[PDB]
Image (cartoon, rainbow over all chains, first blue to last red; front, side, top):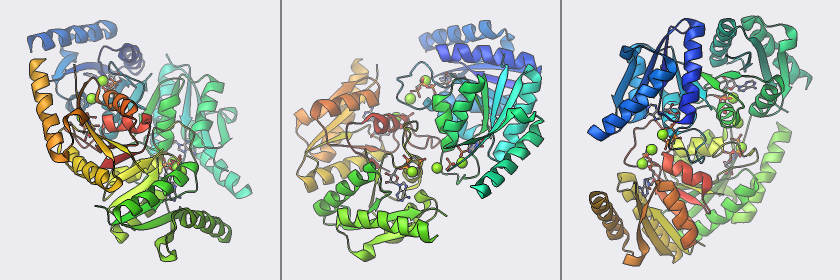
Length: 124
Length: 124
Length: 124
Length: 124
Ligand SMILES: Nc1ncnc2c1ncn2[C@@H]1O[C@H](COP(=O)(O)OP(=O)(O)CP(=O)(O)O)[C@@H](O)[C@H]1O
Ligand SMILES: Nc1ncnc2c1ncn2[C@@H]1O[C@H](COP(=O)(O)OP(=O)(O)CP(=O)(O)O)[C@@H](O)[C@H]1O
Ligand SMILES: Nc1ncnc2c1ncn2[C@@H]1O[C@H](COP(=O)(O)OP(=O)(O)CP(=O)(O)O)[C@@H](O)[C@H]1O
Ligand SMILES: Nc1ncnc2c1ncn2[C@@H]1O[C@H](COP(=O)(O)OP(=O)(O)CP(=O)(O)O)[C@@H](O)[C@H]1O
Ligand SMILES: [Mg+2]
Ligand SMILES: [Mg+2]
Ligand SMILES: [Mg+2]
Ligand SMILES: [Mg+2]
Ligand SMILES: [Mg+2]
Ligand SMILES: [Mg+2]
């Protein structure tokens, strides 16, 4: 099972735990791992986003072509990449940088769980 | 990663897909797999519940001592078993027998996601 | 505004607060108030359900023809009555008898909020 | 009932419907109505935010001192104003400008529903 795994990374402590889990899943299933980081609607925003994505590439060890910067609402970006890469599993945190502890699950995780093309592994 | 995996099984088509995923995860991580099925508050209810649990034991191949019938609100039962068995991953469906398609995620999955002691793998 | 108001009543302390709010809204808007209580799939279940509905009729003062017992998943029952009675506002508790405090909003309120034909007033 | 009503306004079509409902509720209950619009973390952001708040003041007719610009995560801002103004009812849309139709309820409405000091009237 699981030939392609997609990690959604936002640089939060939950996403660093999710990156560890995704690296472990890819090794255990012999899968190809893709990491993605979305930025929302300049040079400054892209520099910041590239650095966050660099961190995800460093924690997972994936090749450059498998670490993607995407633009837009995070969940939409994650879902489009997942359909494009034919992901069999999406790994993401239950919460992220914007956590206040008032939602039961972060809004981008909620959206992905509702529309995902495959199983989603939520990491606390 | 993942030494103990807990599958929450309600006999729905989502939970049969979740049982396949949990069997595959346990084999890939060399983990011990526990399957649980909760029944809500007689002889008839227990007979029905034992049969549903038998199906989960047949699809996963776990030993008898690792297939548990529990009582109460499903999510509470799942969470207590998970803390008791020191589960490192809970696998459950996004929806179950009571699905109407109006919730974004079933209520028992919502409760587990909010209170789980470990990552939760949601299977559609 | 609001000519017909529907109260969804389950006999919980939240629903008793919601009944007070619904009585106050109906008086303030000069509206017709309907109270509904759903029971899930005998003589015993119906006796219990009629008594809960009697309590809602006593707290709101509505006429008998405007206090309805319905069957099925609560939210489905509430929504069908609301479309049937052309309700302009549904008043219900944020939580109910089955509250464990783990959901952000009870599952029947979640379903109604997602599919309602009109505004929904959530009472804590 | 309801002596102080707080409308959370984001300039979306749902919030314009919510403003109509809030104006009608304030008139029916003889209540004081407060409208609030939050902006997230310059001159440009404040100009845009003041114009959105002007629209809410125009649709509800409230006095200047009762139309407030607030800063921060919207739900936090709404909740703090509600405790400060001792609001007895918060009226807000089920969805807003960022709606994609994938959440069951928008994230700021979710947060307010979970932490509100009073009933919340959700307007579709
Ligand atoms: N820009 C982004 N790029 C990639 N993944 C993202 C992302 N934003 C969020 N995620 C993923 O979603 C997970 C859950 O975070 P989410 O953004 O849903 O909640 P949050 O705690 O930040 C509150 P909010 O719903 O207001 O954003 C993160 O751990 C991460 O895996
Ligand atoms: N009695 C039970 N025992 C074990 N697991 C259960 C269970 N009930 C539900 N689950 C687990 O929860 C998953 C999601 O189903 P859930 O019960 O949350 O939603 P549902 O679609 O049945 C609507 P509802 O929230 O009304 O019950 C199921 O696939 C199963 O893994
Ligand atoms: N059988 C029923 N008949 C009428 N209204 C009901 C109902 N069950 C619930 N409701 C309405 O829904 C409100 C919220 O309760 P809800 O049932 O959604 O959550 P809960 O706290 O009971 C946990 P659960 O989702 O497991 O049932 C109740 O206050 C009541 O207004
Ligand atoms: N900046 C803001 N100021 C005041 N009220 C706001 C607000 N943002 C949202 N709201 C209120 O919340 C309601 C629901 O919108 P919400 O922002 O929760 O969902 P949304 O559809 O914009 C998706 P998202 O959760 O990504 O923002 C809006 O109709 C409005 O009443
Ligand atoms: Mg976030
Ligand atoms: Mg169920
Ligand atoms: Mg209930
Ligand atoms: Mg239920
Ligand atoms: Mg919004
Ligand atoms: Mg957001």
